[PDB]
Amino acid sequence: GFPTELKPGTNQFLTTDDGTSPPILPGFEPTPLIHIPGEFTSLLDLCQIETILEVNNTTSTTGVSRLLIPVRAQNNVDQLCASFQVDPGRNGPWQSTMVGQICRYYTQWSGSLKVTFMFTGSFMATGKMLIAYTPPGSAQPATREAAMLGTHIVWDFGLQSSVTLVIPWISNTHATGIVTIWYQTNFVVPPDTPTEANIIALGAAQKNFTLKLCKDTDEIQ
Amino acid sequence: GFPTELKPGTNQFLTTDDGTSPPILPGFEPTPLIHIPGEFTSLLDLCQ
Amino acid sequence: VNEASVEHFYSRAGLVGVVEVKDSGTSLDGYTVWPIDVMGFVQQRRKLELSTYMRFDAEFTFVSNLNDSTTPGMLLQYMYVPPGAPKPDSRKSYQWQTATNPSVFAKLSDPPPQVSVPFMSPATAYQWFYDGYCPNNMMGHFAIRTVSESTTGKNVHVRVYMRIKHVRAWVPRPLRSQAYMVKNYPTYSQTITNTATDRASITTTD
Amino acid sequence: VNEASVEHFYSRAGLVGVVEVKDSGTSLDGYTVWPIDVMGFVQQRRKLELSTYMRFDAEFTFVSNLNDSTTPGMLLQYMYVPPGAPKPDSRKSYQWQTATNPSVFAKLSDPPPQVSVPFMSPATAYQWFYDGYCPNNMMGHFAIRTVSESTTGKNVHVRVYMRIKHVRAWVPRPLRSQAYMVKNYPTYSQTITNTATDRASITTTD
Amino acid sequence: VNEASVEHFYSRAGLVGVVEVKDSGTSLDGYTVWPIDVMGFVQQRRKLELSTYMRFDAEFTFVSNLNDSTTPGMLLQYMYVPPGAPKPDSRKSYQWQTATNPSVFAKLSDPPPQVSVPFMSPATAYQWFYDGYCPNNMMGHFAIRTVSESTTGKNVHVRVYMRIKHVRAWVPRPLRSQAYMVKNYPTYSQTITNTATDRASITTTD
Amino acid sequence: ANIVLSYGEWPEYVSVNRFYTLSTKSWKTESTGWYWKFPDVLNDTGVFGQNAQFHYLYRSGFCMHVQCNASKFHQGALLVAAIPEFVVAASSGLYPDFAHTNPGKNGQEFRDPYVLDAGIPLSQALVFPHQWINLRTNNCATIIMPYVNALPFDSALNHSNFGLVVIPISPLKYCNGATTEVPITLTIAPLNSEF
């Protein structure tokens, strides 16, 4: 009522505040709304779309060639082919996907991920491959006989065209996993057929994923 | 109640605003109204 | 969660531009105009171009000060002109007194003025990309005058903050990897830069 | 729609006149009177003459300032005199102290004063056109004084804004195409001007 | 009783540090940063180390003044940066305009500003003792700037008060009898001092 | 087959509703891609061209199908995407000419596929209603597209609702003796058209 006394905090303007302001054009009416088909309301569900990953980030390779993994036939049976880390928010292969560009506007995240491989070769090409994942806080395997012990999955691209694996659970802030590709069996080819092929990486997120703190991004334009 | 704090927008005069002002002649009464025949209320019906 | 929302993504106040009215030295005038925009800074451009169609309201705040953080009690006038209307052109022109250009009066030593503006558009949403055939989405202007007869000799610095409410975004699109060059146009330089950092080999790591 | 209404057509604030009380130089006086009007500007004349009979209330706002947009703390007095009453004639005349001339007191450094006045008329409505046989519709006056003993030497500039509420218009009439010449009379010049722009031929267009 | 409570033991306001921004003499800068802490004074250290795990909220108050208890009307800016973010490094650097570093504006002649901050931690409680293998419990910083173009020549003294709400303590431990030497570490001197005063004999008293 | 409905909604409101087979494009080892503005690709052909150029207003949906014709000794992979409001930028007069902006029914070849000729990474052009073509799996792709627009009933000779884009990610390669160019064919079928 009438007997009021003012308290500390008066006459201050806080940017992170919401209140009431009078309208400047009373009586005006806006255009009626209609139904535009597409509509995204939650920002978190944009990370469920699977984009392509850039694992060929090596100097002397430019253009669109930095997106494919070359596999040959003369190569031996037991040796490494490619490897990359898991960190989305950090720099590297995960910089060309919608998970690793929306995780630069936040600070903390946790959950599981998803990687899908695809083979593009001739119809009459056969062979096998080995994919492994080393848990956080360990050493990269030196031979395929050691990567066979942990978590892995065999893949015969002569009978299947795409395979998928799921990381169990990761949580970083602001030492974090590794995945490797090994040869198991060579690459067989009939006469009058090319002896080259390529792979795609197709990274994505999962349904258990949260972001917890807002901050401005650093990769300006 | 008593513990109140003022907020931005204080002491400003906005032309396109409506509020309350005290009367200057309390107790005065105006002339009673009667029925003048013609009456236009909507401006849009003058275009017909 | 609530923090990973479109509603919370765009719900913050922030600077959009600084305006200074000069009445000293080689320039002796009392008025300054400013075309209101939403994409005057690069960071807000890359955050507002994750979508194509949007619809919202706006709230504006004005902070004004001298050149030495002093606040005397001189009077000032803020006027907003809707799109499709002439703008003032002199310290004491005729347009400063019109009943349809909403104006407000406040002093220099007072809590900052705060006003709200509705959704002004002849369509059902704003468009940042228009495939068909000086901001594109015209919204209005702000004319600021110091009410005085003769010159004053003191300059005034003004900042402005904008809050947006009731956001609605419809169709998404990827972000931008190339450097911005021109306003209102997506033209990019001829030296294409790779999106990802480089590495010595595909079988090496730290 | 709501925007195409008589209620919204006339519902806005706007300037009606500027008054300056001078107490410096060749003129050393402390008071100034102003006969309140509603048709002191051409634009409001053409908008108020779309009808013949009207009835409404009025709200008045006062903004006052020095000649350099400075607001010291000197005191001022605003007094309203109803029609049919003597008006002050000196800086410290007797009429400045009467219990029936509603007066108000306010300082120069404060939020602007705001007051309301009822519908003052001996008929049932105002008339802009009177076929029978210094405003015609007398409403009152406003006397403004600075409370002081001797002279001050500082001039004061005062503007006034009026809002009207509860409008009622009865019979319409066409607008005006000829230039205004005199107040309170519809006299027009002898060089009749055509209402429409000209064209080269009745069978041509652009 | 109610007075012998954990809730009332910690429920008071009190000084935590003094900050002075200098813009005169050999040092001409406009900004000053301060790492927020809770254990900057010995008495609050011995009262906060009766427990091991704690969880609470905080409320901060700012009182600012010149060097002669005078309060002119110059403007000032207070900004809080969350942990894991760059801090300003110049009078007019880029970080002074970001939409995610909550900032507030207030004048020098006004009631003191008052703000609240939530419980900021990646665990379920704060730890004063950590047996595993520049405050330890990082919470943020406070950057204070005077909004001006050039230098001012006037220094400003600022004090800060903190209130804590909704306290929760879990496991107790004995108090401290040795003198404090270093911050963030319990290192003690080599001359062990007895906890109790001395007496001439075990069979004597006064 | 594996038909994809863009955004999950059909438009839902004899002579002008029939299949239109466009010109065939040749795929080589060196190739960048092609694109087509879709409110205009048919602004010069059939009855639809006539009533679009005459009437002021226009609205419609579309259905598109892409076909390949190769053998089991060839290798490659393509990507087919649809982009609402596909604005084409110019590299460094700040003004692309008419040809790139409004190509005929034959379309325009991409200049810089990596940035999608608009400064767009092309590593993220999968949020759009896309589909894949692999030369060892299948040879077809179908897409439905409703009428997306802010203001209903817009022009047909001054607006471009969307665009269709085909890009080879993996390069074509073969062995000696084989044909050195697999053809690609595109067809359109207006659905729920109004004027």
Image (spheres, coloured by chain):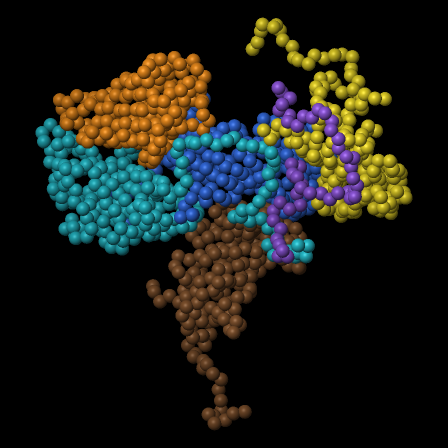
Chain colours: A cyan, B purple, C blue, D yellow, E brown, F orange
Q: Position of residue C48 (x, y in %)?
A: 45, 37
Q: Outermost residue, bottom direction?
A: E203
Left or right, residue F144 beside residue E126: left
Specify whether residue A21 is in view: yes
Residue sitting nearer the eye, F98 or D132: D132
| Residue C43 x %, y % | 46, 39
Q: Most extreme residue toward the right, as rendered?
A: D94
User: Which residue sits at x=13%, y=45%?
Assistant: A78
Q: Residue at x 27, y 36 (%)?
A: A67
**Where does the N terminus of chain F fall, quadrant-wise?**
top left
Residue drawn 78% across the image and 35% down it: B31
Q: How many marks?
A: 0
Q: Residue at x 18, y 33 (%)?
A: A121
Image coordinates for residue D154, horizontal then vertical, percent: 80, 41
The relative height of residue D91 versus residue F149 in the rendered view (above or below) is below
Q: Is residue D71 visible?
A: no
Residue F93 locus on image (x, y percent)? 44, 23
Q: Is residue D34 left or right of residue E127?
A: right
Q: Using residue A115 as the reference point, say whether residue D67 is left or right of it.
A: right
Q: Is residue A26 left or right of residue D113?
A: left
Q: Could you say which is closer to the camera, residue A29 or residue E28?
A: A29
Q: Which quadrant of the rendered structure holds the C terminus of chain F? A: top left
Q: Splitting the image into 4 quarters, where does residue F85 fall?
A: top left
